Image: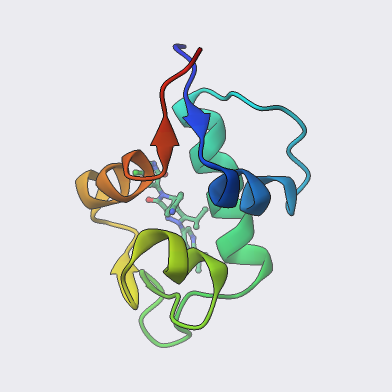
Amino acid sequence: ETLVRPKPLLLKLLKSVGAQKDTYTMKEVLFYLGQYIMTKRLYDEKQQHIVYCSNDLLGDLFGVPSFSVKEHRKIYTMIYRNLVVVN
Ligand SMILES: COc1nc(N(C)C)ncc1-n1nc2c(c1C(C)C)[C@H](c1ccc(C#N)cc1)N(c1cc(Cl)c[nH]c1=O)C2=O
């Protein structure tokens, strides 16, 4: 319910899936990141909980080649490294 402010490059990713504002709830950020993953088919076909994000903007932002969608705490870490103070 509190608002977060994405850094420019995370904001660019969000806007690529139709987001139109500067600040978001965490639930909204997750929804759009999810949309990005699914519409770009970044998940592995055999192990569908694994997202392969090397050579993609998402991998650039998160600083990892891959991650599991089951690892929610690590997902929050990676999102938080891409936020700035809300002014
Ligand atoms: C490959 O992934 C999936 N594949 C399938 N297939 C049918 C193949 N179905 C569901 C998922 N899936 N599971 C979860 C999520 C998805 C989609 C929306 C990416 C989201 C989610 C994961 C990562 C980010 C980031 N960056 C943002 C949202 N997510 C969540 C992650 C967190 Cl932290 C909180 N709540 C969530 O639902 C999950 O558990």
